[PDB]
Image 1 (cartoon, helix red, strand yellow):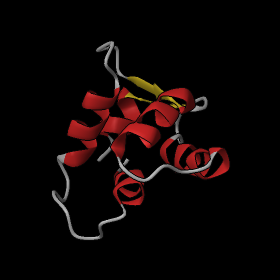
Image 2 (cartoon, helix red, strand yellow):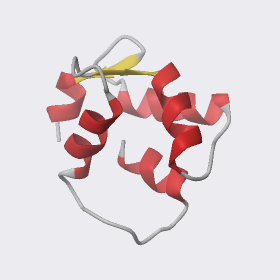
Image 3 (spheres, rainbow, N blue to C red):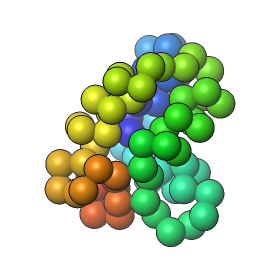
Image 4 (tube, rainbow, N blue to C red):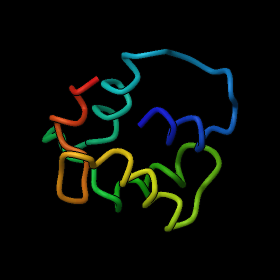
Length: 80
């Protein structure tokens, strides 16, 4: 989630170093369950500041889902 944040804002000097993985994922899951899938990445890509393409958001899922099934859960959020 750190590289997706810097990519969507486009300003390479903004806020945090650690802590941001827990604050960015918990403000992403509005239902409080704790599971981000590729469709919620589309909602946040448009609402942040500078939107990406379908293929580029899927490279962000592959770096985030190393121990999962195509979505980032609680175990890849706390692994920090």
